Structure formats: C-alpha cells, structure tokens
Amino acid sequence: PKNPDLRIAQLRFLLSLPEHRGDAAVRDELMAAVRDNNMAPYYEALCKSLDWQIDVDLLNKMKKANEDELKRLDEELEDAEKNLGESEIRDAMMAKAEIGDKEGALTAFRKTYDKTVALGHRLDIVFYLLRIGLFYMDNDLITRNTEKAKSLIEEGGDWDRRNRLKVYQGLYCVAIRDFKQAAELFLDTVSTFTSYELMDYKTFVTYTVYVSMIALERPDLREKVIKGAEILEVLHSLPAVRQYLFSLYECRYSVFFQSLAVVEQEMKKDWLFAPHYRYYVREMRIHAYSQLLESYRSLTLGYMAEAFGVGVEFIDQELSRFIAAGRLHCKIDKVNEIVETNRPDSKNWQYQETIKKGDLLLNRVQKLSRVINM
Amino acid sequence: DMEAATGQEVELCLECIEWAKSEKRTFLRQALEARLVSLYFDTKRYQEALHLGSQLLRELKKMDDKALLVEVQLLESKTYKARAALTSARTTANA
Amino acid sequence: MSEKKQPVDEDNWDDDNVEDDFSNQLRAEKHGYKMETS
Amino acid sequence: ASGAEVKGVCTEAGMYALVTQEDFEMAVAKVMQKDSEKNMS
Image (cartoon, rainbow over all chains, first blue to last red; front, side, top):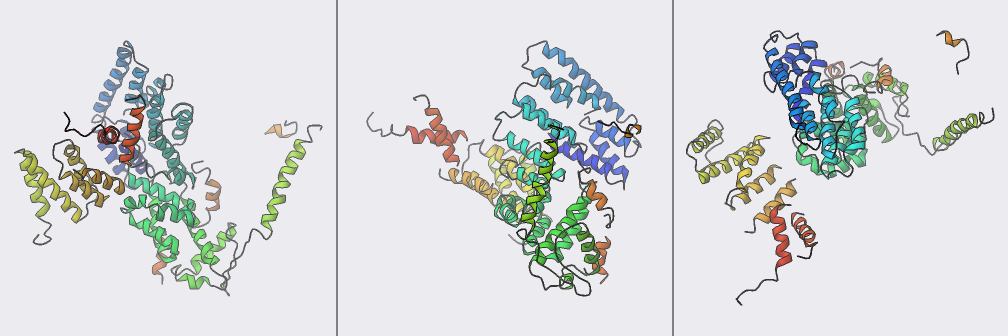
C-alpha cells in the first residue's frame, strides 16, 4: 500500500525541495497525522518544516496511540508465536511494523529478514523496503532490498510480481540518471496497470517519458511511444509531453523550447531530481541540434533562430559552452553562421579505438606482466 | 436531450440515486447508474467515470441480469486494455 | 605500498562532475523571458 | 477424466480468454460435448 505512502514521500520532497511555504509541508504532514496514525510525518515536519505550530499534544496523543499500537504489536509477537506460525508471526509483525518513529522500522526489519521464508515473506519485504527508501530520496534501501530479493524473492516468482520488481528497478533507473534501463524495465505496459506500488499509472507515464525521450532513439522512440499505443490509451491523459514527443519526431524546435521550459520547471518541482535534473534539458538541446545540423551543412543558426525563438545569442553562448563541453562535432560561426554534417566514425575513430584500447590494455597487461618477474 | 445545461443534469441524477439508496430498487438504480456514467463520458470525466464503472460492475456480474452487462462493458471500452475489455464484452454478448 | 615521504599526510554524485561542468551555465526564466525580448 | 485433462481444460479455458470459471466451463464444453444427443433416454 505504498501509493498513499508514495504521496507521503512526495510530501517529504515538498518539505525538502520547495521551502516556499513551509506550512504547506506542515499542512499535509498534520493532515496525514490526524488520521492513519502517521506520526513519522509529524516528526518529519517538526524537523525540516515548521516546528509544529500547534502539534505539541494534538499529535502526541496519536503518538501515544502509535505507542500502544507498537506495544500491542510486540505483545502479539509473543502471543502468536505462542502458537505455531510458519514465520507468519514475524511476518505479521514486520508488516504491521512497516507509522510512528523508526521504532516501527527497527521492529519491522529486525523481525522479517531473520525468518523471511518464502517468496512473499520477501516479496512484501522488498516492496516495503522500496517504500521506506522512497519516503526519502534513498537508493541504499530501494536497491539493497532488491539485492536481498535476488537472494530471496523471485526464484521463479509470479508472471505478475516479478514484473513489479523489475518496474521497481526501472523506477530507480529513472530516479537516477540511468537514462535507459528505466524504460527498458518500464517496457512492460501489460503488467503495471494499477498496484499498491503504482502511486499513479499517470505518474508511471511521467517517470516513463522522463526516461524514454532519452533512451528511445528515433526508432525506439516511435517503437515505444507511437507503435506502443498501449501507453497511448492512457497517456491520452497527459497530452503536453505527449505532443512534445510528437514534435520530437518532426523536430519542431520552437515548441521544443516551449515544452522544454515547461518540463524544466516540472523537473525543478518533481521528486528524486532536485540535485541532478540539470543535464536532461541541455541534453535534449544538444541532441536535437545534432540531427538538425545533420540535415545538411550550408545552413545557419539564424534560419533556426526562428525555431530557437530569438536564439542567436542564446545558442551563441549555449553551443559555445556545449562544444566547450565537448559535444556534437559540427561547424558554426557568427560572421558566417555555419552549419555542418561531419564526424564519420569510419574516418579515423572507428580505426582509432583500435589503439585507444590495444594500448590501454596493452600496457595494462604489460605492467601486469612486468611484476610477474619484476 | 434538450440542451447542454450542465447545472442540473448530473445533480438531479445523483438525487434519485440517493432516493434509490432510500428505497432500494435494484433495476431502477441500475437504470440510473448506466446513464450517469454515459453522462460522465459526455464531458469525458477522467477517473470518476471509470470509478463508477468499477463500483457497479462489482455487483453486475455478481447479480442475475445479463443484458445491461454487455453495454457497460462496452461503454468502458470507449473510455479505456480496451482490446481486453472488448473481448470480454464479446463472450458475454452471445447469450 | 606507500614507502615515501607521503606518509606525512551517485544520486547526484554521479551527475556531480557534470554539475560542476554545469556550474557555469545559467544554473537553472531568462531563457523563457528571451522569448518576449523580441 | 484421464488425469491431465484438468490441464487441457485449463488450455481450452485460457484460449477462450485469449481465467474466469466460465473459461473452464467453455473449456469442458469443447472437451465434454459428445457426450451429447439425447432423445434416447
């Protein structure tokens, strides 16, 4: 049941990334605390957001409710293992202990991993470790648990749950700058309709496109977005980035820049991207310019400055620092405003890699085969 | 079928649904639910058209009737997986 | 070994080298405000 | 039925769905028909 707790993770990100109205973080943390016993939101807001303007006792009462809850959980721990349970005593205690403080976590994972017995004992354990990680912007939890899973969960698994583990892997692959294996693991589209792991299938589409407009080269672009009309029956609900992708074939750079600003702000205000979203947009820029110049040579940026908006000075500094970033072999001027189609690998590079590696590894093995004697 | 007067259409429909909560006629409330979800598609409502189709089809294949089940499976195939929902409407339609 | 004088002495971390390479370009509107500049 | 016939009915069911109880019902319906043809009671 991590979808609402994924929304709570987004609450924590709102507490983290936007410090505009810290009461809004206090707002939804108190809203998640007044019911569902969720006190961890309340300590979380106490720390980063406001210091709980009025929640000294209004949430300490529900903290005492969580205290009685945890104490009766740990009492039924012995009341039920009094009876025989096929690791199901510890299974129930780990499930119910995955609400209040990290007390619930330490009575959750210290009582499952020791007697995790079958696929489900770790199926839910790894799903909910992914959730306890995703509440913050974690990667140790949400993939170390996948390591345990590889040791524990699947072993054949389901045609349903294993696709879910793979979609977890892809969900972090888009959370991190792993701009391909997300869409690879999000290539299912027949096994992630709706789940307690899918906070929103439309948000599934968001994470998917925010890795597919990069992983999917033009053939894979049309393969998954266009051809794969399975996601289209659902991405019919978010036409902004969809039409962006539509232009992403005809290469309409004006609307490219419109939606580029749009998605830039969007990522600026979206989870698990705050300290990294910098490249994606300028990467889209350079990649599109690549094909645009690849059209032909005797062309101008000014002829494209229209598509660039008023992009003469914009792209001046832009492509200056981009070629300075060592990108996109091409030619362009100011007094001449050139465009180019160049950089064939089978000119020298397809022959330069030869020594690039047969000297790197050559001397690697050389010194490696030097200390064999000296 | 007079005019797109959206101020009273969906509200009057929810009213006698609440009357059907208070009177409990099965065939009359199903008559009201089927047009309401058709009215939801007329403005193409995003989730609640699907959520009304979910909450009614928890009971429709559970209850005894067969004939209107074919329509509400078919109405979901417009709002949608749509190949899957159409084929389930295919095998129901033959009886 | 270190037998010399010297004994005297991915979340964003992966994207961090590019970030310091991004530390010189409009870190993150004037892009979009340039639309109405002309 | 000769043991694995449950598997075959599963195959017949899944084919209809391509698995509700009705699937296996139609599965046996293909499987079991003939026997049919009353009017000889």
